Image (cartoon, rainbow, N blue to C red; front, side, top):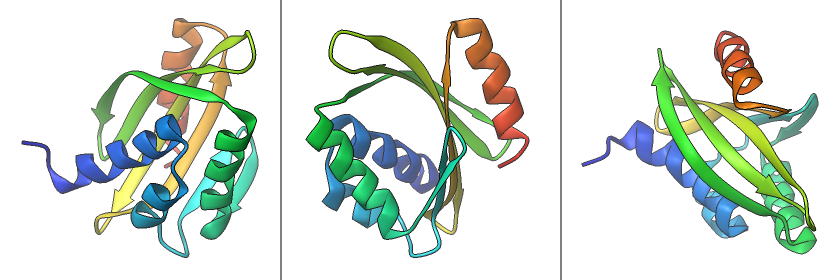
Amino acid sequence: HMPEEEKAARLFIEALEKGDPELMRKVISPDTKMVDNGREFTGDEVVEYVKEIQKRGEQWHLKKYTKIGNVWVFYVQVDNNGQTEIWVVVIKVENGRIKIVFIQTVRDEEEAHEAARKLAKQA
């Protein structure tokens, strides 16, 4: 039902939702780039990132997502120890693997849409 491109991106989010590094390993490639609020990760660093989520006990929940051009935009609720934020996650898949992921934290669903537009245009 879901195309491979969508499956890939969706799996990336699933990994974070479940804090599952092995799941993440399956989706990324040595040149996969992720930028989390300015901080760049590459390759295995992204898997290590997922290990940190789990360790921290951080809870990622997907609210909804959409396709803008050739990038995927996910809106995720993130929780750490009695505090809740919306994070925007923009993914570009190339040849069935994650090329580039942009993550940014935002303070309302309106600024979410703004960041999504902005980050999409960079991906």
